[PDB]
Image (tube, coloured by chain):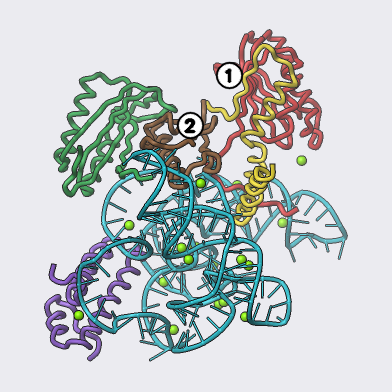
Chain colours: A purple, B brown, C red, D yellow, E green, F cyan
Amino acid sequence: EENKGSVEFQVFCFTNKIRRLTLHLELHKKDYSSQRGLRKTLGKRQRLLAYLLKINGVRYKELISKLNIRELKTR
Amino acid sequence: PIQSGDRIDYRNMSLISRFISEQGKILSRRVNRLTLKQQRLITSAIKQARILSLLPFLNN
Amino acid sequence: ARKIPKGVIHVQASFNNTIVTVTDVRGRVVSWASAGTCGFRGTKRGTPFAAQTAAGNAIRTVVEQGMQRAEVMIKGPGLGRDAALRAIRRSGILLSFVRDVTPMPHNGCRPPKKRRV
Amino acid sequence: SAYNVQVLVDDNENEERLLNRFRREVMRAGVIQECKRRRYFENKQEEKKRKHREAAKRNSRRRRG
Amino acid sequence: PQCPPGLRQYETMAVLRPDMTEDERLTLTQKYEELLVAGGAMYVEVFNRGVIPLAYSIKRKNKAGETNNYLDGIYLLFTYFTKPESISPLEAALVTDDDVIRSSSFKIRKRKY
RNA sequence: ACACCAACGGCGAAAGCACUCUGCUGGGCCGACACUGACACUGAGAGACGAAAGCUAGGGGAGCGAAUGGGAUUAGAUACCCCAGUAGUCCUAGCCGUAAACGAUGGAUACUAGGCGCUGUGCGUAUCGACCCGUGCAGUGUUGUAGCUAACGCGUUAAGUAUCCC
Ligand SMILES: [Mg+2]
Ligand SMILES: [Mg+2]
Ligand SMILES: [Mg+2]
Ligand SMILES: [Mg+2]
Ligand SMILES: [Mg+2]
Ligand SMILES: [Mg+2]
Ligand SMILES: [Mg+2]
Ligand SMILES: [Mg+2]
Ligand SMILES: [Mg+2]
Ligand SMILES: [Mg+2]
Ligand SMILES: [Mg+2]
Ligand SMILES: [Mg+2]
Ligand SMILES: [Mg+2]
Ligand SMILES: [Mg+2]
Ligand SMILES: [Mg+2]
Ligand SMILES: [Mg+2]
Ligand SMILES: [Mg+2]
Ligand SMILES: [Mg+2]
Ligand SMILES: [Mg+2]
């Protein structure tokens, strides 16, 4: 289905699992074990994005405008 | 040699009472010659049964 | 005073003394014998011998009431655990059951520290 | 009610066999060693000491004999 | 065969007072079957084994203030498929009743040894 | 506070985590090509977590128990022992950021005998379901060859042979 390994699909799966995790992190604030994972996965997504910005400028801008991902920290 | 062919639970009392002491203590894995996985499952079972008063903590 | 045919003997054995009480199944105390009440004091009060004379001393009054069968209750780590049983036997009273009631917490109140001696 | 050790004496009763039956019941549940153990408080360290000591004692007594 | 579509499998044991009739028992049955089915349970399978002496004496206070000391007991066994969301109230709803002296519920996992 | 289970066993980044159960969720590992195609490793600054004692505010207070008091012991005893016993230990919301926070061993990768063990799975065999055997991985434990080391020792979980960053 599409490419399940494609950059943009992966970044999506990540952004989505993160915004999902957000609710759990809001309800139970004392769970640090889970937050540590969040920070890890966010790291992954951020990496892929940096990579994709290097490789293709167009696909990148399209993607972060599409998935409502916050603009990059290289500015 | 000895083995579990039937699903072990808290409601098979025959089973669990094999692995229980006279005083109702749980016998160790080295004695019962069970795989670690088994032994754990037994243990939790025994505790659950103990709560449901199927087997006694202490005796009369 | 009360003539009761069957009752129970509680024997508490602690390290400093052993108490022996005699009762009946109604959960009612008839007569008791302490190793300290026999004219023993702190050291000797723990020895298995003082427990022997304690036991003998209670069973005096229990045959005086004319009782026959008894259960034995043993509570605590001390020496009299074994000693008292002997007197219960040689005092020529039928022994029904012998149980150990030493309480074992299953977890709980955090004990005193270790004496550095 | 409750009980730890159950020694029922039959009417064949003699003192020494009774006394020793009971003694081996107490050895069997390990109650006196138990109440010498809970007499005072132990930090986790003396618990690991006791576990290694006792467990490897009876274990090496099982592997030598 | 049993096949849940987006549900969790469950077992529940309940222990009831021995002083109960079969009509009061079936009324409880009916009631809890209804709570389950009202909670999205596809397949309510209930089974009964009543009147066994307990391992130990249990105490239950009533709404009438009674202290009830028991020896026997009524064991009700429930295999049912409910959403993980909806198992929440059931357990307390079992605790709250005076007739239910000891309740416990387990999730069932497939055994592989 | 959680006896037995408990084990030279399990998970965790570390701190740590154990009566039972349910629910929300973090990782791990394994087998298949299903896919992307170097997206890697490390990390100055910076951020999060971080035993216990401690502190602010509100609760809670059984046991234990600094401080404190009595009783002893002693030349003395502001200690050891005994009898009492307040903070604190517990919960909620925060602060503090230190420990022999120890494997006294930063991280990643590659490569170099074995023997005996365990935990997870996978394969073939054994029966056609439990073993059983041999094996493939992933971690974990004990002896030990080469080599290393001032010795002790370490030894595929290196303190070996090399490369990169702190
Ligand atoms: Mg003394
Ligand atoms: Mg690990
Ligand atoms: Mg999980
Ligand atoms: Mg290509
Ligand atoms: Mg730094
Ligand atoms: Mg902090
Ligand atoms: Mg603290
Ligand atoms: Mg202060
Ligand atoms: Mg005190
Ligand atoms: Mg003083
Ligand atoms: Mg006190
Ligand atoms: Mg706090
Ligand atoms: Mg430091
Ligand atoms: Mg250091
Ligand atoms: Mg084998
Ligand atoms: Mg390996
Ligand atoms: Mg070593
Ligand atoms: Mg070595
Ligand atoms: Mg070196």
> Horizontal placement of E105 versus C73: left or right?
left
Do the residues bearing badges 2 and 1 touch, measured as CB atoms within 8 Å? no
From mark 2 to mark 1, how far is it between C-alphas?
Answer: 39 Å
Q: Residue D19: x, y in percent?
A: 72, 24
Q: Quadrant of residue C29?
A: top right
Q: Residue at x 67, y 19 (%)?
A: C31
Report if residue C20 is visible in the image. Answer: yes
Question: Is ligand 11 closer than 8 angstroms to the Cβ of mark 1?
Answer: no
Q: Residue at x 21, y 72 (%)?
A: A5
> Relative to D16, is D31 above or below?
below
> Which amino acid lies under the numbered mark 1 shown in the image of this protein?
Arg
Question: Disc 2 vs disc 1: which is toward the camera?
Answer: 2
- In the picture, the quarter occupied by the C terminus of chain A is bottom left
Question: Is ligand 15 closer than 8 angstroms to the Cβ of mark 2?
Answer: no
Q: Residue at x 75, y 15 (%)?
A: C91
The residue that disc 2 covers is B18
Q: Quadrant of residue D36?
A: top right
Quick one: B54 or F7, which is closer to the camera? Answer: F7
The residue that disc 1 covers is C28
> Which amino acid lies under the numbered mark 2 shown in the image of this protein?
Arg
Quick one: F109 or F71, which is closer to the camera? Answer: F109
> Horizontal placement of F29 versus C88: left or right?
left
Bin the neighbour count of mark 1 within 10 Å (Cα to Cα): few under 14, some 14-19, many 20 and up.
few
